[PDB]
Image (cartoon, grey):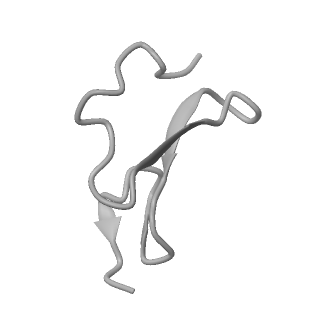
């Protein structure tokens, strides 16, 4: 389970590529305003 496999064009903005194995796998930390786990929902804040 997870998506470490490729961290290419894996984040959209805040995208601080941090392995969240902890809870799941590899993810990005998006800005306070961009979330959804990929800063794909740039909730412009």
* Residue 23 left/right relative to 5: right
Q: Is residue 3 above or below residue 44?
A: above
* Residue 25 left/right relative to 28: right
Identify which residue is drawn at 31% across, 83% down.
44
Identify which residue is drawn at 33% across, 45% down.
11
Q: Quadrant of residue 9?
A: top left
> Residue 15: where, in percent of width, then height?
39, 51
Q: Quadrant of residue 36?
A: bottom left
> Residue 3: where, in percent of width, then height?
47, 22
Instruction: State the residue in front, 20 or 16.
Output: 16
Tally of numbered tags:
0
Q: Quadrant of residue 14?
A: bottom left
Identify which residue is drawn at 45% across, 69% down.
31
Identify which residue is drawn at 39% across, 86% down.
45
Q: Which quadrant is the N terminus positioned in?
A: top right
Q: Is residue 22 above or below residue 40?
A: above
Instruction: State the residue in front, 24 or 12.
Output: 12
Q: Is residue 30 above or below residue 4?
A: below
> Residue 25: where, in percent of width, then height?
60, 26
Q: Residue furthest left?
A: 9
Q: Residue furthest bottom?
A: 45
């Amino acid at each position: 389970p997870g998506a470490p496999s490729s961290y290419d064009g894996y984040c959209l903005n805040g995208g601080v590529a941090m392995h969240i194995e902890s809870l799941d796998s590899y993810t990005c930390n998006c800005v306070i305003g961009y979330s959804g786990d990929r800063c794909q929902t740039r909730d412009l804040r």
